[PDB]
Image (cartoon, rainbow over all chains, first blue to last red; front, side):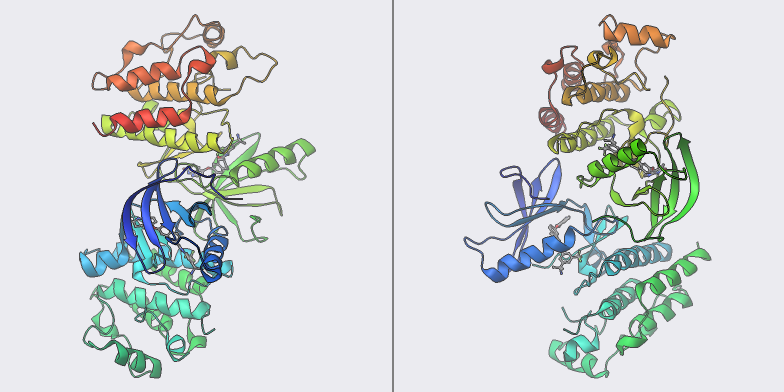
Length: 253
Length: 262
Ligand SMILES: CC(C)(N)c1cc(NC(=O)[C@H]2CCc3ccc(Oc4ccnc5c4CCC(=O)N5)cc3C2)cc(C(F)(F)F)c1
Ligand SMILES: CC(C)(N)c1cc(NC(=O)[C@H]2CCc3ccc(Oc4ccnc5c4CCC(=O)N5)cc3C2)cc(C(F)(F)F)c1
């Protein structure tokens, strides 16, 4: 059992609030992260969503997965993970425009695929992989999670509309691959969210692969296309994705 | 359940090998560390020790505690944990002789204290806390474990971290939260002096006899001068020959988290 004894966790500075939960930095045997539900009485749907997240995270134990540490049901619903120092991959690529070099982008790719493989082996479908959910711990270690509190990462069959599968996550990983090698989001020239949803859903729109860094190895570019295949079945599974990056990582540095 | 699906682990490089198992660098969803038995069929009392280690590791989910990932029985009894790059605190201090900064020395203690506080709360006595069992992953993160043999052996069982009540080897069980504290106090000594205690004595049995009867004690006057007053005071508290005059880990952690921001 992973229930943290009552009255141990001291909540500190308020990080991020969302329509559902709120995150605080806190103290429990050092620095910890705390995702709380700020409600006086939780509904059955809230209670159930809590029990899912906990049920899932307790099955994870891997360097590329955000480390789960415990939960508290009284006084308020809370999930406790390690405290990570750094930013999301989203932040580095699109906000503070960190210029990583090729070797490092590939290491991020590998590590993300490393953890993704882990989740899939245990029948865990992420359902919402995106650069924002990939936290870069100490600007070294990928820690995949759900920092949720959308659309660019959604595969066609998820937009047309349970349509989630191992392959739906690969497409999201494909978009993350795109972000890494371009440094930009897909469809940056289109400024109408509703139209993107329509177009990607019909196959009219695809990420423009021509925008890759000149020094992105061909093997990376070819893997990317495989992951973005509009049809579920054509997309490689993560064991093959990893193998492909691990073959490419070989003859490069 | 944390049994790893049969035959997924590939064992590679060979790191260390006592009589109680062999440590390998392996592969399971990335680079991992593997400790396993190399006998045909394990004895009843070897299977037990395996079951205890797994029993303990399964209860730990902490940044400063070495990350247990899974175990396997077929083909062999094996424990899988995360792979760590770098070397123990012992190596850095007494073999390669890294000249760490004071801020970092305090951080190294702050983390070991964090880790120990966690284990003690989960009702886990370490029983062999020493700078050999303090791994410095990527030279910036303390991972506490029992690396018996996966790291270099200490100068002299290892004796330097044992409290007086532990060395006297009384038939009644002497291991307590405080004995871990004393070991921490010796680790602190190691950090603050860059040296091992009782370095001017060359007889193992003398050291044993004298620490036990309280005729020997670490020489406090050996510490760096840029070492805080609040640290020396604490390090003396942790080494107090009286068992329960030694601060428990929550109070230790608070004291280090105090001066850390001044
Ligand atoms: C519901 C389901 C099945 N889709 C699902 C939920 C999650 N949920 C999480 O990962 C949550 C857990 C609670 C929690 C708490 C604190 C938190 O915020 C941290 C953590 C560490 N460091 C920092 C911050 C804040 C911002 C900073 O600066 N540091 C983040 C999270 C993330 C994971 C998975 C996965 F394992 F499959 F990926 C799957
Ligand atoms: C039985 C009991 C209660 N005394 C006990 C045993 C342990 N046992 C461990 O920690 C073992 C587990 C198996 C294992 C396997 C591989 C290994 O070698 C690693 C690991 C990581 N990285 C590296 C290496 C090699 C050298 C390098 O370069 N990297 C180390 C260990 C350490 C922990 C605890 C504690 F956590 F409570 F303190 C308590």
